Image (cartoon, grey):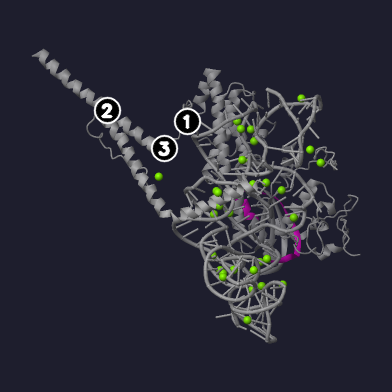
Amino acid sequence: PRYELALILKAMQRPETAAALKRTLEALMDRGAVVRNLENLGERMLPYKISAHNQRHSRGGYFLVDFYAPATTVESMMEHLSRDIDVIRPNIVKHPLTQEVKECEGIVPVPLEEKLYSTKKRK
Amino acid sequence: QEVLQLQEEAKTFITRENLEARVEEALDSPKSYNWAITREGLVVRPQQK
Amino acid sequence: QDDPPPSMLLLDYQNVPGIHKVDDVVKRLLSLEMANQKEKLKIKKMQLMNKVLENPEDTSSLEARIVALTVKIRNYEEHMQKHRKDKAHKRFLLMSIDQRKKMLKNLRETNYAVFEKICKELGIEYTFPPPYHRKAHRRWVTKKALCTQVFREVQKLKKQKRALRAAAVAAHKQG
Amino acid sequence: KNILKIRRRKMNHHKYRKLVKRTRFLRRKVREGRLRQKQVKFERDLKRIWQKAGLKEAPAGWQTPKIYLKNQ
Amino acid sequence: VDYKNVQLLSQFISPFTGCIYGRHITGLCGKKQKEITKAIKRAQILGFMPVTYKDPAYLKDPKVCNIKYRE
RNA sequence: AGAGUUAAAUUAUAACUAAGCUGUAAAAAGCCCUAGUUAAAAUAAAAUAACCCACGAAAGUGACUCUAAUAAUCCUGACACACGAUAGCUAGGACCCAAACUGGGAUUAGAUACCCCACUAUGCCUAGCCCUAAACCCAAAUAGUUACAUAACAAAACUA
Ligand SMILES: [Mg+2]
Ligand SMILES: [Mg+2]
Ligand SMILES: [Mg+2]
Ligand SMILES: [Mg+2]
Ligand SMILES: [Mg+2]
Ligand SMILES: [Mg+2]
Ligand SMILES: [Mg+2]
Ligand SMILES: [Mg+2]
Ligand SMILES: [Mg+2]
Ligand SMILES: [Mg+2]
Ligand SMILES: [Mg+2]
Ligand SMILES: [Mg+2]
Ligand SMILES: [Mg+2]
Ligand SMILES: [Mg+2]
Ligand SMILES: [Mg+2]
Ligand SMILES: [Mg+2]
Ligand SMILES: [Mg+2]
Ligand SMILES: [Mg+2]
Ligand SMILES: [Mg+2]
Ligand SMILES: [Mg+2]
Ligand SMILES: [Mg+2]
Ligand SMILES: [Mg+2]
Ligand SMILES: [Mg+2]
Ligand SMILES: [Mg+2]
Ligand SMILES: [Mg+2]
Ligand SMILES: [Mg+2]
Ligand SMILES: [Mg+2]
Ligand SMILES: [Mg+2]
Ligand SMILES: [Mg+2]
Ligand SMILES: [Mg+2]
Ligand SMILES: [Mg+2]
């Protein structure tokens, strides 16, 4: 997967929720995006209260949208997400699974540094 | 091998129709990533419910 | 301007078996469409080195490096268009335009015909470095401009004063 | 220590800036005064050429612009 | 390390402050410390995790770090 | 280099509540359109992580995200070319807070200062200049060696 969409949404009832998600992925599929998956992380009370669209929210629903999109596009979708009345905060991150795991071989122990000061028979 | 992986996931993708399915499913099955650690390197995932 | 078409199938997937039968979704995923820009630059690199070169394999070939460098320059130029305030990348571009000139001086000294054909292909022109780099300042540019025009005049005057002698001596010889 | 060299500089600089404040307009004269010599010598430099190249007038379309006195 | 598991990132944060413990406490490689830090900051701006205190839910979870506050 | 975003704090401005609040070695002036609490945009600046030592040619760079992206099959090289902290200059915006200047207040023989209080150019953005630093790691670049060898001190001595 290429890109990841963290959707924090205004907590609603089910129908309204469904609507919001649907039109979101519609917008994406219109900017040229291929949607992999949809992961509902639940409705949580937000860590802190978020003010957007002249409403200050306590709780919210959490969603994760993996998708492939062309480079040029990401701005467009960000704009159309910011415009949206029920998105309580958008974001788009390079999907975690493009990033490689380069093996910690372990701790390479660092030896004390020597030959800093000159040898001097002082005092 | 890569090309065939993607060939396999092409069956599982979300397309214009499956929206109606997928969305209805996403709400049905909440999934967690929440995940922990033990001093031995071991993981303890969320306690069984 | 050239245009590595949206559907072009990123380089590393080009020659693998059984591609065209594959459904349009995955083709769309491995297209230049979904690509980073780096990919498009791999393509441009390939195409240029095919059109221009002799032996696609040699990296170390003076020619090869000139072509590659030229690709990256052309890229820095677009990145220059969109960011005019970016001093860093201006630096890269201008170092690189130069290094290309360096290796071109190498071709022009060593293998002539090849150098020639590269200059033809890549639209690069070789202007010999002019002796005496001196900042031309207002006083000098002005005094030279004047002098140039004084010359341009004195040859005119000399021309006429000898032309009336041509006319006079010919009109005396004729009758 | 080496501060004792810097002290001198520090003083000499300060004592100079102070000077250039009092003297400012006297200075301003003598600067422009020499710019009007410059532009003139410059002119003569070129005049010399017509007269040396045999032309009577300065060549066609020559206003001989003022570089040194350039302002704003 | 993902910015998604806030439990994990909570494990490396001071409960009362919301501080991020240093290597000399957490005891991590260079790359894993850095990884954790960035992950946390991401989790804070995206708001999966709060800034100024350890989410109470996770106070009762296993404790990794070497700090002794209460003596 | 772009484009988008904000967690802590602060401020407008309301709701209450108390008369004080601020400020130093000690005070005074200052403000009570003040202060504590509860709400809350903009602007500005980026705790911890950092006991890390990465990235850039250097200046410099450490909130978040995405886009673009880090010259050279790699020797040296200018008065040429392109950059160059702060401060400053030009035009237009911004203005929480800081603050040269200046005006009060103390201190003082004096106090054009150190302390206090306000407030300004200015730090901020966009575009254009200016081209200076203890621009210093005071240690030129590129290959080497640890042989020979202690002026002193500092970061040990040297080839090409
Ligand atoms: Mg010693
Ligand atoms: Mg002197
Ligand atoms: Mg003079
Ligand atoms: Mg900008
Ligand atoms: Mg705030
Ligand atoms: Mg407040
Ligand atoms: Mg307030
Ligand atoms: Mg006190
Ligand atoms: Mg009083
Ligand atoms: Mg610190
Ligand atoms: Mg450092
Ligand atoms: Mg790139
Ligand atoms: Mg390089
Ligand atoms: Mg060089
Ligand atoms: Mg400067
Ligand atoms: Mg400035
Ligand atoms: Mg101001
Ligand atoms: Mg304001
Ligand atoms: Mg103030
Ligand atoms: Mg006074
Ligand atoms: Mg006294
Ligand atoms: Mg004192
Ligand atoms: Mg003010
Ligand atoms: Mg600045
Ligand atoms: Mg410095
Ligand atoms: Mg120093
Ligand atoms: Mg020096
Ligand atoms: Mg040098
Ligand atoms: Mg070099
Ligand atoms: Mg040796
Ligand atoms: Mg001795």
Task: Name the residue tied to disc 2.
Answer: D53
The span from disc 3 to disc 1 (Cα, nearest Å) is: 12 Å
Q: Residue C137, labelled with which disc?
A: 3
Of badges 2 and 1, the one in the foreground is 2
On the rendering, which quadrant does ligand 14 occupy? top right
Residue type beneath disc 1: His
Residue D53 in picture, x, y percent from top left: 27, 28
Q: Position of residue E11 (x, y in %)?
A: 83, 57
| Mark 3 Cα shell of 10 Å, populated few (<14), some (14-19), many (≥20) | few
Q: Is mark 3 within 8 Å of ligand 3?
A: no
Q: Nearer the viewer, residue A39 or F41?
A: F41
Residue under the image location 52 percent in, 18 percent down: C112
Cβ–Cβ under 8 Å for marks 3 and 2:
no
Q: Which residues are magenta?
A: A25-49
Disc 1: residue Cβ within 8 A of ligand 14's nearest atom: no
Number of other residues with Cα within 10 Å of mark 2, as a class: few under 14, some 14 to 19, many 20 or more:
some
Residue E31 at what x, y percent from top left?
Answer: 78, 46
Question: Do circles 3 and 1 both sit on a common chain?
Answer: yes
x then y, percent, for residue C15? 67, 30
